[PDB]
Image (cartoon, rainbow over all chains, first blue to last red; front, side):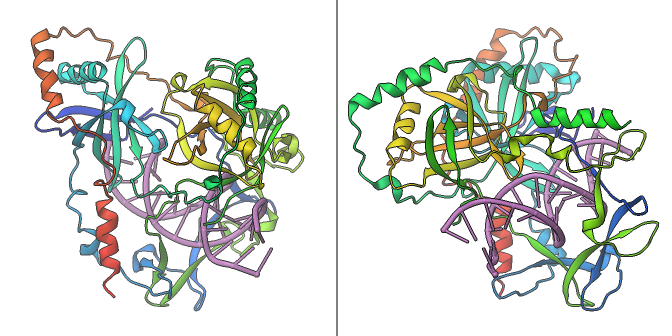
Length: 227
Length: 226
DNA sequence: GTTTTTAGTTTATTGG
DNA sequence: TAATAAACTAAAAAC
């Protein structure tokens, strides 16, 4: 129950205050690592193999390994090349219809809950996005790194909010140069009908209530078992 | 290019041999941890706080820590209490229209292509999913873990390849507990009607070609210093 | 064997 | 004080 980001939407000169929230959280049980012999929590020490001594974090540096195994100590100015990391405002690039986006790149989502002082300007954007059904492709800065993200509105009955989903880059989808589907397809139309009623008998409507994390609940029962 | 697992979609009687591929492979640059005094790589080795002696992994146990900080001695039989890990087939539950699912739950995507020489069984389902235009929800199993996923098709011009996306559980979405947004705001229609074309001034169409990871390319340019 | 892929696990900022 | 990204181990299936 705590926000993550506190900035504004920098589309032109609009600057609506927004309180980004973590839309989803990993309810999956995260365990801990302990030593059964002596009941001791485990800690990792980073010790060089060749010499064998402990060091503080501040004396090491990032190193990119190429095919030949070269090591490069990245200079501070090279990392500081981006002026967008200095930026702390969501920059808006364009607006695209919601049906013109592909559902594969939607990686992680966050809420956009505004500040009540100027909520009138926020509700205008929300109602406009509900009207034109236009998704917004926005540059997103977070955790000192920049991710391409989308901005769109999802009704929740009582109140409408806009939601931000971080997409992968367009170069982050492998092109499937598959040769097996270039084979000529020979299907008699008599067979095509059978697949119809087979799926149609399995008809249903999306019911999120019925679905459960089957393993996680049975493992959670273990937690209550011991204590 | 190497596959991940080789099973087969198995609901009722249909059993189409399939070869799952990784749809997205993060090409973001990954770095090792290195310091100059050794001029070499770094290793993580595990020690006990109280003992102070290096211990092997094989004599350590899973532990869950509640608010009280109590231990949990995880055994093998209780971990094996769920036999879905033994399954190596994609189990299908139902089919749902593509418009009845919302795009938030998609987490990671995987491709689906046949393995056997006969591809008729694949193409039947592929053409079926492009006619009824309905998704399919599976009880996907992968890497001794079970995750809910869904089947749907992305026509790539020449092939009707269908893909699988792993969705989060319905309890994995936090409720929108904002009691401030329900406030009634009176908007003059003039503001909305002049904001209409204001938004439309920035209208465009999706052009993935011109979008790039600027930071990744600048950093890569730094790597090519050699 | 093989290097990829993937899930499990401290850990080190940073921002409410 | 809690969430997100670095970076490594540690299985662990395909062929």
